[PDB]
Image 1 (cartoon, each protein chain N blue to C red):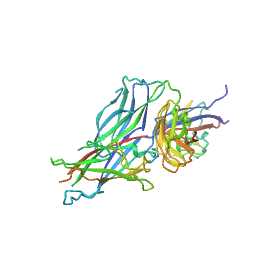
Image 2: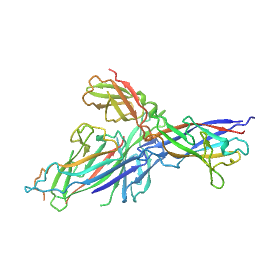
Image 3: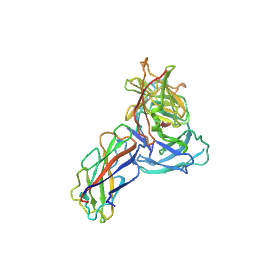
Image 4: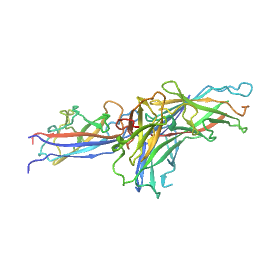
Length: 135
Length: 147
Length: 201
């Protein structure tokens, strides 16, 4: 055999916290690789969800019990360097609907910012599920 | 058919150590006729910043070439070597008297957690155990030992 | 008017794995004037900073290599050194020039040690003896306390060395106090989780 969606991840460079306790935007947090889907699967057939459930954004949380959070967006690039926007928690950027690369597709997790307070240094995780429709 | 997969994505955030310092000159100083300067002359104001909250008053040490514990020493730029001492002191959240280390010792108070964001210290004239003052200079290293 | 100074190190501690070739740390001149960056290692020269002295133009960043060449360290415990990074600016009227000496912990960690500090942070035990709050640290790591509270009052913190203790001065009013709270600083420089415990006899 049956079709199997795969989802791997490669972590990018460590993120430096600024003196205001926030982080820069557009930092490569890391790279998701989605594979194992049918030919002709479009970006709107792909939905990354997490527990926070914020439409369009993934939320990372600190591992220290202090609930420090930051958000990120998920954006791939096609061959001519236009944005590929998959659904994140049900939602999408308008205009970034695109057929996925054959076999597998990389998506960049790009930093937005702190969500509710100064950030503390440490480890941050987010448990992501991907649903791919029309398989 | 909807097919699913999952992954726990991760990131490391790092806190750099930033230390900043602002010096604000106080009024110019008046010799009094006997060759004295007045006491408690606010020579200048230091604002120490950038540090992480929890940084304490003993993690901060102002040192100069004289190395006189508890006091900073200013010397004339002439040839004649006239000197005076100052102290470095501030206030906590209870308006109690606090000092950082100066050449390795505190003048006044218990160790405290410094104020959030930034902390003011005032450089205050003591006297001149010599006597007869006639540009006076100092070169001061502010060492902060981060937690 | 007022003069301004500032040195930034890219991290607030350096975890150095025993026997590693070296590590790099970013140094930034956050000021509008060039400085000389002067870097030195102090005990609590096996470690070498390169370059020991170099010029850094306004608003620029460079990196230092910290490298171990020799040295003999316990393998049952962490060792502690200090990396100091000093920004030297260019050269009765009172004229003072300042220089910031920004100092961070260099923690020497044997690969022989299992785990990390945040996994043993909860194991601190606490005691009042001779008017002082005493912490015991049974782990092989420096317990770098970043927040400490006793009977609801804040105590300036300090590291607890590995397999050892530290005594803290107490402010009056903590007669029959029993409840200690603490956070350590994790390896990335952040305030970790809150632990809470009663003092023992």
